[PDB]
Image: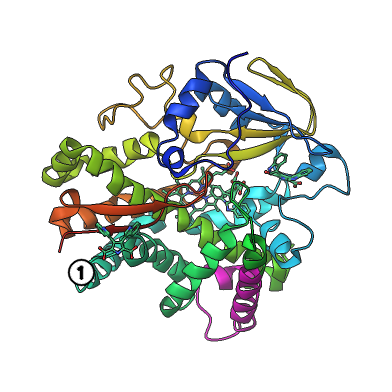
Protein backbone atom coordinates (compact mmCIF):
# COMPACT_ATOMS: atom_id res chain seq x y z
CA UNK A 1 0.00 0.00 0.00
CA UNK A 2 0.87 3.65 -0.02
CA UNK A 3 -1.70 5.58 2.03
CA UNK A 4 -2.36 4.87 5.73
CA UNK A 5 -5.76 4.76 7.40
CA UNK A 6 -7.98 7.85 7.14
CA UNK A 7 -10.13 9.54 9.79
CA UNK A 8 -11.33 13.06 10.69
CA UNK A 9 -9.63 13.11 14.14
CA UNK A 10 -6.73 14.91 15.78
CA UNK A 11 -5.95 17.04 12.72
CA UNK A 12 -3.58 19.99 13.07
CA UNK A 13 -4.98 23.49 12.57
CA UNK A 14 -3.11 23.74 9.25
CA UNK A 15 -5.06 20.86 7.72
CA UNK A 16 -8.35 21.82 9.35
CA UNK A 17 -8.05 25.22 7.62
CA UNK A 18 -7.09 23.66 4.27
CA UNK A 19 -8.22 19.99 4.22
CA UNK A 20 -8.53 19.77 0.44
CA UNK A 21 -4.97 18.57 -0.27
CA UNK A 22 -5.74 15.64 2.06
CA UNK A 23 -9.06 14.70 0.42
CA UNK A 24 -7.30 14.89 -2.92
CA UNK A 25 -4.48 12.48 -2.12
CA UNK A 26 -7.10 9.97 -0.94
CA UNK A 27 -9.65 10.62 -3.68
CA UNK A 28 -6.98 9.97 -6.32
CA UNK A 29 -6.09 6.58 -4.81
CA UNK A 30 -9.66 5.33 -4.32
CA UNK A 31 -13.25 6.63 -4.05
CA UNK A 32 -13.84 4.75 -0.78
CA UNK A 33 -11.42 4.07 2.07
CA UNK A 34 -12.11 1.86 5.02
CA UNK A 35 -10.79 2.39 8.53
CA UNK A 36 -10.94 -0.34 11.13
CA UNK A 37 -11.74 0.51 14.73
CA UNK A 38 -10.58 -2.10 17.22
CA UNK A 39 -13.09 -3.69 19.61
CA UNK A 40 -16.83 -4.08 19.16
CA UNK A 41 -16.51 -0.79 17.45
CA UNK A 42 -17.72 -0.96 13.86
CA UNK A 43 -15.64 -0.15 10.77
CA UNK A 44 -16.07 3.18 9.01
CA UNK A 45 -15.97 3.74 5.25
CA UNK A 46 -15.01 7.22 4.07
CA UNK A 47 -16.31 8.32 0.69
CA UNK A 48 -14.27 10.90 -1.22
CA UNK A 49 -15.81 10.91 -4.68
CA UNK A 50 -18.75 13.05 -5.84
CA UNK A 51 -20.62 10.14 -7.44
CA UNK A 52 -20.15 7.91 -4.43
CA UNK A 53 -21.08 10.67 -1.97
CA UNK A 54 -24.26 11.09 -4.00
CA UNK A 55 -24.84 7.35 -3.59
CA UNK A 56 -24.29 7.60 0.17
CA UNK A 57 -26.89 10.34 0.60
CA UNK A 58 -29.32 8.61 -1.78
CA UNK A 59 -29.38 4.84 -1.16
CA UNK A 60 -32.19 3.91 1.26
CA UNK A 61 -30.33 1.06 2.91
CA UNK A 62 -28.20 3.67 4.64
CA UNK A 63 -29.92 5.09 7.74
CA UNK A 64 -29.11 7.36 10.70
CA UNK A 65 -29.40 4.88 13.60
CA UNK A 66 -26.41 2.68 14.50
CA UNK A 67 -28.65 0.53 16.74
CA UNK A 68 -30.97 -0.22 13.82
CA UNK A 69 -27.88 -1.04 11.72
CA UNK A 70 -26.34 -3.46 14.20
CA UNK A 71 -29.68 -4.81 15.52
CA UNK A 72 -28.14 -4.57 18.99
CA UNK A 73 -30.09 -2.97 21.88
CA UNK A 74 -26.73 -2.27 23.55
CA UNK A 75 -25.44 0.01 20.79
CA UNK A 76 -26.41 3.71 21.12
CA UNK A 77 -28.88 5.10 18.53
CA UNK A 78 -26.74 8.25 18.25
CA UNK A 79 -23.00 8.90 18.95
CA UNK A 80 -23.33 10.20 22.53
CA UNK A 81 -22.42 8.15 25.66
CA UNK A 82 -25.30 6.88 27.80
CA UNK A 83 -23.61 8.71 30.77
CA UNK A 84 -24.92 11.92 29.28
CA UNK A 85 -28.69 11.39 29.35
CA UNK A 86 -29.86 14.98 28.75
CA UNK A 87 -27.48 15.23 25.79
CA UNK A 88 -28.52 11.84 24.41
CA UNK A 89 -32.24 12.74 24.64
CA UNK A 90 -31.78 16.08 22.91
CA UNK A 91 -29.64 14.67 20.10
CA UNK A 92 -31.64 11.54 19.35
CA UNK A 93 -34.56 13.91 18.90
CA UNK A 94 -32.92 15.79 16.03
CA UNK A 95 -34.70 15.41 12.67
CA UNK A 96 -31.35 14.83 10.93
CA UNK A 97 -30.89 11.57 12.89
CA UNK A 98 -34.40 10.18 12.40
CA UNK A 99 -35.54 7.51 9.94
CA UNK A 100 -38.82 7.32 8.04
CA UNK A 101 -41.66 7.19 8.96
CA UNK A 102 -40.98 9.34 12.06
CA UNK A 103 -38.60 11.46 10.00
CA UNK A 104 -41.25 11.92 7.30
CA UNK A 105 -43.96 12.95 9.75
CA UNK A 106 -41.73 15.53 11.44
CA UNK A 107 -40.18 17.09 8.32
CA UNK A 108 -43.67 17.28 6.83
CA UNK A 109 -44.95 19.23 9.83
CA UNK A 110 -41.88 21.48 9.71
CA UNK A 111 -41.31 22.21 6.00
CA UNK A 112 -44.29 24.52 5.45
CA UNK A 113 -42.60 27.01 7.79
CA UNK A 114 -39.45 27.35 5.66
CA UNK A 115 -40.96 27.75 2.19
CA UNK A 116 -39.55 30.00 -0.58
CA UNK A 117 -42.57 32.21 -0.03
CA UNK A 118 -41.84 32.65 3.66
CA UNK A 119 -38.13 33.29 3.06
CA UNK A 120 -38.98 36.04 0.57
CA UNK A 121 -41.06 37.84 3.18
CA UNK A 122 -38.16 37.50 5.59
CA UNK A 123 -35.47 39.23 3.46
CA UNK A 124 -36.15 42.93 4.17
CA UNK A 125 -35.87 42.07 7.84
CA UNK A 126 -32.83 39.78 7.48
CA UNK A 127 -31.40 42.89 5.83
CA UNK A 128 -32.13 45.32 8.67
CA UNK A 129 -30.70 42.80 11.12
CA UNK A 130 -27.37 42.53 9.30
CA UNK A 131 -27.21 46.31 8.92
CA UNK A 132 -27.84 46.85 12.65
CA UNK A 133 -25.21 44.24 13.55
CA UNK A 134 -22.56 45.89 11.34
CA UNK A 135 -23.68 49.30 12.58
CA UNK A 136 -22.66 48.23 16.06
CA UNK A 137 -19.39 46.66 14.95
CA UNK A 138 -17.82 49.98 13.93
CA UNK A 139 -18.18 51.08 17.53
CA UNK A 140 -15.27 48.71 18.14
CA UNK A 141 -11.55 48.73 17.22
CA UNK A 142 -10.85 45.03 16.50
CA UNK A 143 -14.25 43.49 15.83
CA UNK A 144 -14.82 39.77 15.82
CA UNK A 145 -16.83 39.00 12.69
CA UNK A 146 -18.07 35.74 14.24
CA UNK A 147 -19.40 36.81 17.63
CA UNK A 148 -20.23 40.28 16.35
CA UNK A 149 -21.91 39.23 13.12
CA UNK A 150 -21.77 35.74 11.56
CA UNK A 151 -23.38 34.12 14.60
CA UNK A 152 -25.95 36.76 15.76
CA UNK A 153 -27.48 37.21 12.31
CA UNK A 154 -28.72 33.63 11.80
CA UNK A 155 -29.50 33.19 15.51
CA UNK A 156 -31.72 36.28 15.54
CA UNK A 157 -33.43 35.03 12.38
CA UNK A 158 -34.14 31.53 13.65
CA UNK A 159 -35.01 32.97 17.08
CA UNK A 160 -37.88 34.93 15.54
CA UNK A 161 -39.17 31.89 13.62
CA UNK A 162 -39.02 29.96 16.89
CA UNK A 163 -40.64 32.85 18.70
CA UNK A 164 -37.98 33.29 21.39
CA UNK A 165 -36.41 36.51 22.87
CA UNK A 166 -33.96 38.38 20.66
CA UNK A 167 -32.25 39.41 23.91
CA UNK A 168 -31.16 35.79 24.44
CA UNK A 169 -28.98 35.57 21.33
CA UNK A 170 -25.71 35.51 23.32
CA UNK A 171 -26.93 32.94 25.85
CA UNK A 172 -28.30 30.80 23.00
CA UNK A 173 -24.97 31.02 21.14
CA UNK A 174 -22.80 29.97 24.10
CA UNK A 175 -24.94 26.94 24.90
CA UNK A 176 -24.97 25.92 21.22
CA UNK A 177 -21.16 26.07 21.22
CA UNK A 178 -20.93 24.10 24.49
CA UNK A 179 -23.19 21.42 22.99
CA UNK A 180 -21.11 21.36 19.79
CA UNK A 181 -18.25 19.64 21.73
CA UNK A 182 -20.37 16.52 21.61
CA UNK A 183 -19.94 16.50 17.86
CA UNK A 184 -18.24 13.28 16.74
CA UNK A 185 -15.04 14.77 15.37
CA UNK A 186 -14.17 16.88 18.40
CA UNK A 187 -11.27 16.63 20.85
CA UNK A 188 -13.23 15.63 23.95
CA UNK A 189 -10.14 15.33 26.19
CA UNK A 190 -11.62 16.85 29.33
CA UNK A 191 -15.31 17.79 29.76
CA UNK A 192 -16.43 18.47 26.23
CA UNK A 193 -19.20 15.98 26.96
CA UNK A 194 -19.91 17.26 30.48
CA UNK A 195 -20.28 20.79 29.08
CA UNK A 196 -22.50 19.59 26.23
CA UNK A 197 -24.51 17.71 28.86
CA UNK A 198 -25.07 20.87 30.90
CA UNK A 199 -25.76 22.86 27.74
CA UNK A 200 -28.39 20.27 26.78
CA UNK A 201 -30.01 20.74 30.17
CA UNK A 202 -30.01 24.50 29.85
CA UNK A 203 -31.77 24.14 26.51
CA UNK A 204 -34.22 21.60 27.94
CA UNK A 205 -35.33 23.97 30.73
CA UNK A 206 -35.30 27.01 28.51
CA UNK A 207 -37.46 25.30 25.92
CA UNK A 208 -39.65 23.45 28.43
CA UNK A 209 -40.33 26.87 29.91
CA UNK A 210 -41.22 28.29 26.49
CA UNK A 211 -43.84 25.63 25.88
CA UNK A 212 -45.59 25.76 29.24
CA UNK A 213 -45.96 29.41 28.16
CA UNK A 214 -47.59 28.33 24.90
CA UNK A 215 -50.99 29.06 26.25
CA UNK A 216 -50.44 32.80 26.20
CA UNK A 217 -51.54 35.34 23.65
CA UNK A 218 -50.96 32.78 20.92
CA UNK A 219 -48.68 33.49 18.00
CA UNK A 220 -47.34 31.45 15.15
CA UNK A 221 -43.77 30.57 15.62
CA UNK A 222 -42.47 27.03 15.44
CA UNK A 223 -42.99 26.68 19.21
CA UNK A 224 -46.75 27.30 19.06
CA UNK A 225 -47.01 25.27 15.87
CA UNK A 226 -45.26 22.43 17.71
CA UNK A 227 -47.28 22.71 20.93
CA UNK A 228 -50.60 23.00 19.09
CA UNK A 229 -49.74 19.82 17.16
CA UNK A 230 -49.20 17.82 20.36
CA UNK A 231 -52.33 19.27 21.98
CA UNK A 232 -54.38 18.34 18.93
CA UNK A 233 -53.06 14.79 18.79
CA UNK A 234 -49.84 14.72 16.79
CA UNK A 235 -47.35 11.98 17.86
CA UNK A 236 -45.06 14.37 19.70
CA UNK A 237 -43.51 14.37 23.18
CA UNK A 238 -42.26 17.49 24.94
CA UNK A 239 -38.75 16.00 24.63
CA UNK A 240 -39.39 15.85 20.89
CA UNK A 241 -40.46 19.49 20.81
CA UNK A 242 -37.49 20.46 22.99
CA UNK A 243 -35.10 18.55 20.75
CA UNK A 244 -36.59 20.09 17.63
CA UNK A 245 -36.11 23.62 18.96
CA UNK A 246 -32.50 22.73 19.81
CA UNK A 247 -32.03 21.19 16.37
CA UNK A 248 -33.52 24.19 14.57
CA UNK A 249 -31.49 26.63 16.67
CA UNK A 250 -28.14 24.91 16.14
CA UNK A 251 -28.62 23.67 12.58
CA UNK A 252 -30.26 27.01 11.90
CA UNK A 253 -27.19 29.13 12.61
CA UNK A 254 -23.88 27.33 13.15
CA UNK A 255 -23.86 26.40 9.47
CA UNK A 256 -24.68 29.90 8.19
CA UNK A 257 -22.15 31.29 10.68
CA UNK A 258 -19.40 29.14 9.20
CA UNK A 259 -20.40 29.99 5.65
CA UNK A 260 -20.26 33.71 6.35
CA UNK A 261 -16.96 33.51 8.24
CA UNK A 262 -15.20 31.25 5.72
CA UNK A 263 -16.58 33.30 2.82
CA UNK A 264 -14.75 36.34 4.18
CA UNK A 265 -11.64 34.17 4.39
CA UNK A 266 -12.10 32.92 0.81
CA UNK A 267 -12.78 36.32 -0.75
CA UNK A 268 -9.67 37.68 1.03
CA UNK A 269 -7.55 34.99 -0.60
CA UNK A 270 -9.22 35.75 -3.95
CA UNK A 271 -9.14 39.54 -4.18
CA UNK A 272 -10.17 39.59 -7.84
CA UNK A 273 -13.43 37.88 -6.94
CA UNK A 274 -13.90 40.06 -3.88
CA UNK A 275 -13.39 43.26 -5.85
CA UNK A 276 -15.54 41.95 -8.70
CA UNK A 277 -18.27 41.26 -6.15
CA UNK A 278 -17.99 44.71 -4.58
CA UNK A 279 -18.75 46.35 -7.93
CA UNK A 280 -21.26 43.96 -9.48
CA UNK A 281 -23.79 42.82 -6.79
CA UNK A 282 -25.96 40.88 -9.25
CA UNK A 283 -23.22 38.25 -9.08
CA UNK A 284 -23.98 37.65 -5.41
CA UNK A 285 -26.31 34.66 -5.94
CA UNK A 286 -23.76 32.91 -8.16
CA UNK A 287 -20.96 33.72 -5.72
CA UNK A 288 -22.81 32.14 -2.80
CA UNK A 289 -23.40 28.94 -4.78
CA UNK A 290 -19.73 28.75 -5.75
CA UNK A 291 -18.52 29.70 -2.26
CA UNK A 292 -20.61 26.75 -1.08
CA UNK A 293 -19.03 24.32 -3.52
CA UNK A 294 -15.61 25.80 -2.87
CA UNK A 295 -15.47 25.42 0.91
CA UNK A 296 -18.70 23.92 2.38
CA UNK A 297 -19.64 24.68 6.05
CA UNK A 298 -20.38 20.99 6.67
CA UNK A 299 -17.42 18.80 5.71
CA UNK A 300 -18.76 15.39 6.72
CA UNK A 301 -22.04 13.60 7.32
CA UNK A 302 -22.56 10.03 8.45
CA UNK A 303 -24.88 7.18 7.60
CA UNK A 304 -25.17 3.58 8.74
CA UNK A 305 -25.55 0.50 6.55
CA UNK A 306 -28.84 -1.26 7.30
CA UNK A 307 -27.91 -4.02 4.86
CA UNK A 308 -24.80 -4.96 2.84
CA UNK A 309 -23.95 -2.36 0.21
CA UNK A 310 -21.20 -2.18 -2.44
CA UNK A 311 -19.46 1.21 -2.84
CA UNK A 312 -16.25 1.98 -4.68
CA UNK A 313 -13.80 -0.89 -4.20
CA UNK A 314 -15.55 -2.02 -0.99
CA UNK A 315 -18.34 -4.35 0.09
CA UNK A 316 -19.76 -2.55 3.14
CA UNK A 317 -21.25 -5.02 5.67
CA UNK A 318 -24.49 -4.31 7.52
CA UNK A 319 -23.72 -2.30 10.65
CA UNK A 320 -20.88 -0.29 9.15
CA UNK A 321 -20.64 3.46 9.52
CA UNK A 322 -20.38 5.43 6.27
CA UNK A 323 -18.99 8.95 6.03
CA UNK A 324 -19.77 11.17 3.05
CA UNK A 325 -17.04 13.78 2.68
CA UNK A 326 -19.02 16.73 1.32
CA UNK A 327 -15.94 18.91 1.10
CA UNK A 328 -14.11 16.27 -0.92
CA UNK A 329 -17.09 15.66 -3.22
CA UNK A 330 -17.32 19.38 -4.03
CA UNK A 331 -13.71 19.40 -5.22
CA UNK A 332 -13.81 16.23 -7.30
CA UNK A 333 -12.36 17.15 -10.76
CA UNK A 334 -14.51 14.47 -12.40
CA UNK A 335 -17.51 16.63 -11.53
CA UNK A 336 -16.00 20.14 -11.20
CA UNK A 337 -13.07 20.91 -13.59
CA UNK A 338 -10.23 22.91 -12.00
CA UNK A 339 -11.89 22.23 -8.61
CA UNK A 340 -9.41 24.39 -6.67
CA UNK A 341 -10.23 27.46 -8.75
CA UNK A 342 -12.87 29.77 -7.30
CA UNK A 343 -15.01 30.41 -10.38
CA UNK A 344 -18.38 32.07 -9.72
CA UNK A 345 -19.59 31.48 -13.28
CA UNK A 346 -19.18 27.73 -13.23
CA UNK A 347 -22.32 25.65 -12.93
CA UNK A 348 -22.31 24.76 -9.25
CA UNK A 349 -25.94 23.94 -8.37
CA UNK A 350 -24.39 20.50 -8.46
CA UNK A 351 -22.49 21.00 -5.17
CA UNK A 352 -23.67 18.82 -2.25
CA UNK A 353 -23.06 21.37 0.53
CA UNK A 354 -26.77 21.25 1.44
CA UNK A 355 -26.78 17.47 1.31
CA UNK A 356 -29.01 15.36 -0.91
CA UNK A 357 -31.81 12.83 -0.52
CA UNK A 358 -34.44 12.77 2.20
CA UNK A 359 -32.22 14.66 4.67
CA UNK A 360 -31.52 17.48 2.19
CA UNK A 361 -31.03 20.66 4.18
CA UNK A 362 -34.46 21.73 5.46
CA UNK A 363 -33.57 25.42 5.49
CA UNK A 364 -31.70 25.59 2.19
CA UNK A 365 -33.78 28.47 0.81
CA UNK A 366 -33.48 30.28 4.13
CA UNK A 367 -29.75 29.55 4.21
CA UNK A 368 -29.26 30.92 0.71
CA UNK A 369 -31.15 34.09 1.67
CA UNK A 370 -29.04 34.67 4.80
CA UNK A 371 -25.87 33.93 2.82
CA UNK A 372 -26.35 36.50 0.05
CA UNK A 373 -28.04 39.14 2.22
CA UNK A 374 -25.39 38.37 4.81
CA UNK A 375 -22.27 38.72 2.74
CA UNK A 376 -23.86 41.66 0.93
CA UNK A 377 -24.00 43.49 4.23
CA UNK A 378 -20.33 42.67 4.83
CA UNK A 379 -19.32 43.74 1.31
CA UNK A 380 -21.12 47.11 1.50
CA UNK A 381 -20.64 47.88 5.20
CA UNK A 382 -16.94 47.05 5.48
CA UNK A 383 -14.94 48.56 2.56
CA UNK A 384 -11.68 47.30 4.05
CA UNK A 385 -12.99 43.73 4.38
CA UNK A 386 -10.27 42.72 1.94
CA UNK A 387 -7.47 44.95 3.26
CA UNK A 388 -5.28 44.89 6.33
CA UNK A 389 -4.62 41.97 8.62
CA UNK A 390 -6.96 39.43 10.13
CA UNK A 391 -6.60 36.76 12.76
CA UNK A 392 -8.57 33.56 12.81
CA UNK A 393 -8.91 30.41 14.87
CA UNK A 394 -10.69 27.41 13.39
CA UNK A 395 -12.69 25.14 15.65
CA UNK A 396 -11.37 21.59 16.03
CA UNK A 397 -14.45 20.41 14.15
CA UNK A 398 -14.66 18.53 10.84
CA UNK A 399 -18.47 18.38 10.72
CA UNK A 400 -19.42 21.99 11.46
CA UNK A 401 -16.30 23.39 9.84
CA UNK A 402 -15.10 26.94 10.40
CA UNK A 403 -13.71 29.83 12.54
CA UNK A 404 -14.45 30.15 16.26
CA UNK A 405 -13.63 33.79 15.66
CA UNK A 406 -12.18 36.15 13.10
CA UNK A 407 -10.91 39.58 14.14
CA UNK A 408 -10.21 42.23 11.53
CA UNK A 409 -7.74 45.10 11.66
CA UNK A 410 -9.42 47.81 9.67
CA UNK A 411 -10.19 50.59 12.03
C1 LIG B 1 -25.68 27.96 4.48
C2 LIG B 1 -25.96 27.27 5.69
C3 LIG B 1 -26.39 25.90 5.84
C4 LIG B 1 -25.70 24.76 5.38
C5 LIG B 1 -24.35 24.72 4.62
C6 LIG B 1 -26.49 23.60 5.74
C7 LIG B 1 -26.13 22.27 5.42
C8 LIG B 1 -26.87 21.12 5.76
C9 LIG B 1 -26.52 19.74 5.41
C10 LIG B 1 -25.29 19.29 4.60
C11 LIG B 1 -27.49 18.94 5.92
C12 LIG B 1 -27.59 17.41 5.81
C13 LIG B 1 -26.81 16.62 6.87
C14 LIG B 1 -26.94 15.09 6.67
O1 LIG B 1 -27.37 14.63 5.56
O2 LIG B 1 -26.60 14.34 7.61
C15 LIG B 1 -28.43 19.85 6.59
C16 LIG B 1 -29.58 19.46 7.28
C17 LIG B 1 -30.53 20.29 7.93
N1 LIG B 1 -30.50 21.69 7.97
FE1 LIG B 1 -29.18 22.82 6.97
N2 LIG B 1 -27.65 23.98 6.42
C18 LIG B 1 -27.60 25.40 6.48
C19 LIG B 1 -28.60 26.22 7.07
C20 LIG B 1 -29.79 25.83 7.72
C21 LIG B 1 -30.78 26.76 8.27
C22 LIG B 1 -30.69 28.30 8.23
C23 LIG B 1 -31.78 25.99 8.83
C24 LIG B 1 -32.95 26.49 9.47
C25 LIG B 1 -33.47 26.04 10.67
C26 LIG B 1 -31.36 24.58 8.59
C27 LIG B 1 -32.04 23.40 8.97
C28 LIG B 1 -31.63 22.06 8.70
C29 LIG B 1 -32.35 20.88 9.12
C30 LIG B 1 -33.64 20.86 9.95
C31 LIG B 1 -31.68 19.78 8.65
C32 LIG B 1 -32.08 18.30 8.83
C33 LIG B 1 -33.16 17.85 7.86
C34 LIG B 1 -33.35 16.33 7.73
O3 LIG B 1 -32.64 15.54 8.40
O4 LIG B 1 -34.22 15.93 6.96
N3 LIG B 1 -30.17 24.55 7.92
N4 LIG B 1 -28.03 21.15 6.47
O1 LIG C 1 -23.07 4.18 18.63
C1 LIG C 1 -23.54 5.06 17.89
O2 LIG C 1 -24.75 5.39 17.86
C2 LIG C 1 -22.60 5.80 16.93
N1 LIG C 1 -23.01 6.66 16.01
C3 LIG C 1 -21.94 7.18 15.41
C4 LIG C 1 -22.01 8.17 14.25
O3 LIG C 1 -20.98 8.82 13.95
O4 LIG C 1 -23.11 8.29 13.66
C5 LIG C 1 -20.79 6.64 15.97
C6 LIG C 1 -19.47 6.91 15.65
C7 LIG C 1 -18.80 8.06 15.71
N2 LIG C 1 -17.53 7.84 15.37
C8 LIG C 1 -17.35 6.55 15.09
C9 LIG C 1 -16.24 5.82 14.69
C10 LIG C 1 -16.36 4.46 14.45
C11 LIG C 1 -17.59 3.82 14.61
C12 LIG C 1 -18.70 4.55 15.01
C13 LIG C 1 -18.57 5.92 15.25
C14 LIG C 1 -21.21 5.74 16.94
C15 LIG C 1 -20.37 5.08 17.83
C16 LIG C 1 -19.42 5.60 18.59
N3 LIG C 1 -18.83 4.63 19.28
C17 LIG C 1 -19.40 3.46 18.99
C18 LIG C 1 -19.16 2.17 19.42
C19 LIG C 1 -19.92 1.11 18.93
C20 LIG C 1 -20.92 1.36 17.99
C21 LIG C 1 -21.16 2.65 17.55
C22 LIG C 1 -20.40 3.70 18.05
O1 LIG D 1 -21.22 15.16 15.01
C1 LIG D 1 -21.54 14.53 13.98
O2 LIG D 1 -20.95 13.51 13.57
C2 LIG D 1 -22.72 15.04 13.15
N1 LIG D 1 -23.09 14.49 11.99
C3 LIG D 1 -24.11 15.20 11.50
C4 LIG D 1 -24.84 14.83 10.21
O3 LIG D 1 -25.85 15.49 9.87
O4 LIG D 1 -24.39 13.87 9.55
C5 LIG D 1 -24.42 16.24 12.37
C6 LIG D 1 -25.43 17.19 12.25
C7 LIG D 1 -26.35 17.53 13.15
N2 LIG D 1 -27.07 18.55 12.68
C8 LIG D 1 -26.63 18.88 11.47
C9 LIG D 1 -27.01 19.87 10.58
C10 LIG D 1 -26.33 20.01 9.37
C11 LIG D 1 -25.28 19.16 9.06
C12 LIG D 1 -24.90 18.16 9.95
C13 LIG D 1 -25.58 18.03 11.16
C14 LIG D 1 -23.53 16.13 13.43
C15 LIG D 1 -23.44 17.01 14.51
C16 LIG D 1 -23.27 18.33 14.48
N3 LIG D 1 -23.30 18.80 15.72
C17 LIG D 1 -23.49 17.79 16.58
C18 LIG D 1 -23.64 17.75 17.96
C19 LIG D 1 -23.86 16.53 18.59
C20 LIG D 1 -23.94 15.36 17.84
C21 LIG D 1 -23.79 15.40 16.46
C22 LIG D 1 -23.58 16.62 15.83
O1 LIG E 1 -5.27 43.12 17.80
C1 LIG E 1 -6.08 42.73 18.67
O2 LIG E 1 -6.72 43.48 19.43
C2 LIG E 1 -6.28 41.22 18.82
N1 LIG E 1 -7.02 40.65 19.77
C3 LIG E 1 -6.89 39.33 19.66
C4 LIG E 1 -7.59 38.33 20.58
O3 LIG E 1 -7.35 37.11 20.44
O4 LIG E 1 -8.36 38.79 21.45
C5 LIG E 1 -6.04 39.03 18.60
C6 LIG E 1 -5.57 37.78 18.21
C7 LIG E 1 -4.31 37.36 18.12
N2 LIG E 1 -4.30 36.13 17.60
C8 LIG E 1 -5.55 35.74 17.34
C9 LIG E 1 -6.07 34.57 16.79
C10 LIG E 1 -7.44 34.45 16.61
C11 LIG E 1 -8.29 35.48 16.99
C12 LIG E 1 -7.77 36.65 17.55
C13 LIG E 1 -6.40 36.77 17.72
C14 LIG E 1 -5.65 40.24 18.06
C15 LIG E 1 -4.84 40.43 16.95
C16 LIG E 1 -3.53 40.25 16.83
N3 LIG E 1 -3.17 40.52 15.57
C17 LIG E 1 -4.23 40.89 14.86
C18 LIG E 1 -4.40 41.24 13.53
C19 LIG E 1 -5.67 41.55 13.05
C20 LIG E 1 -6.76 41.51 13.90
C21 LIG E 1 -6.60 41.16 15.24
C22 LIG E 1 -5.33 40.85 15.71
Picture quadrant of residue 279 = top left
Q: As drawn, which residue projects farthest toward the left?
A: 279
Magenta span: 198-226
Where does the image place residue 242, in percent across and percent down from the top left?
Answer: 64, 68
Q: Give the secondary structure at mark 1.
A: loop
Q: Please identify the quadrant where the C terminus is shown.
A: bottom left
Quadrant assignment for ligand 4: bottom left
Is residue 196 among what the camera can see? Answer: yes
Is 211 contained in the magenta span?
yes
305 and 192: which is toward the camera: 192
Q: Which residue is drawn at 76% across and 42% down?
A: 66
Q: How is the image coloured?
A: rainbow
Could you tell me how many numbered marks the image carries?
A: 1
Where does the image place residue 86, in percent across and percent down from the top left?
Answer: 72, 67
- Ligand 4 within 8 Å of disc 1? The answer is yes
Where does the image place residue 119, in percent across and percent down from the top left?
Answer: 38, 56
Residue picked out by circle 1: 141
Category of crowding for the residue at label 1, using alpha-carbon neighbours closer than 10 angstroms: few (below 14), some (14–19), many (at least 20) = few
- Please identify the dominant SS of the magenta region: helix
Picture quadrant of residue 148 = bottom left
In the image, residue 76 above or below residue 307: below
Amino acid sequence: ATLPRFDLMGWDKKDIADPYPVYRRYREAAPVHRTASGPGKPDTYYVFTYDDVVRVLSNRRLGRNARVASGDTDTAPVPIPTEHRALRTVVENWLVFLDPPHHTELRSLLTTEFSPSIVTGLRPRIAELASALLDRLRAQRRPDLVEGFAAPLPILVISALLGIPEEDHTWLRANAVALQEASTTRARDGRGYARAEAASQEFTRYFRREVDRRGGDDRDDLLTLLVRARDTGSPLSVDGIVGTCVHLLTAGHETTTNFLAKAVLTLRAHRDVLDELRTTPESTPAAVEELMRYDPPVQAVTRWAYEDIRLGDHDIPRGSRVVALLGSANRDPARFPDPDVLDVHRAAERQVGFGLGIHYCLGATLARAEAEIGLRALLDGIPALGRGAHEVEYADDMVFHGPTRLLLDLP
